[PDB]
Amino acid sequence: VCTEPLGLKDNTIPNKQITASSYYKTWGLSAFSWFPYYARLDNQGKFNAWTAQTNSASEWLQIDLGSQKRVTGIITQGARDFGHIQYVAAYRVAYGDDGVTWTEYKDPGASESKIFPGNMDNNSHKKNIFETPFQARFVRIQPVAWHNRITLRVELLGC
Image 1: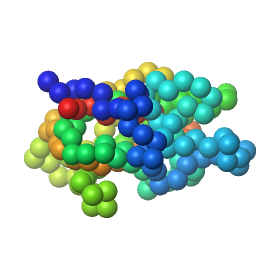
Image 2: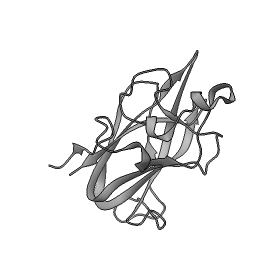
Image 3: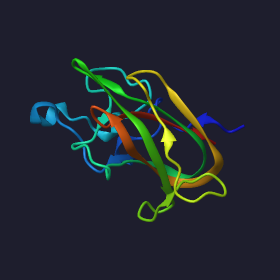
Image 4: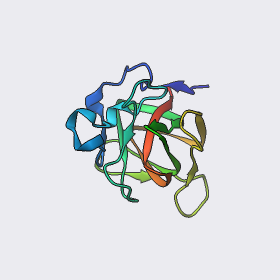
């Protein structure tokens, strides 16, 4: 039920609707920017993912679904960077309607926001189905733990 791709992999969701706290540039070159809108599931290529500019705990990847939608799950991947794999091992999920106010996701009846189990390599998919689904227009992925660098490729599930 529900559990459908919301538009990241198939590019249904436009680039302008995907932003982040910051992003990385290989060799400091603007052309080699690991843009937030590259964080699409199964994205192929050489700069095929979002990588934060810095590795801090306050980085985030924001997705503007364009409208209020039912969000039931999420899927993430890391990505390779030359001779190095990079991926987010753990993360939190926040959501809202206006993209300025956020609600940290948390399992039903629980203190402290949920820290989701993430990836363990560069291409394997990690899917998490929310115990309690929610409705929102904006969703943010907040990496908590990472391997080498904060790097993501995402797909949001719902209907």
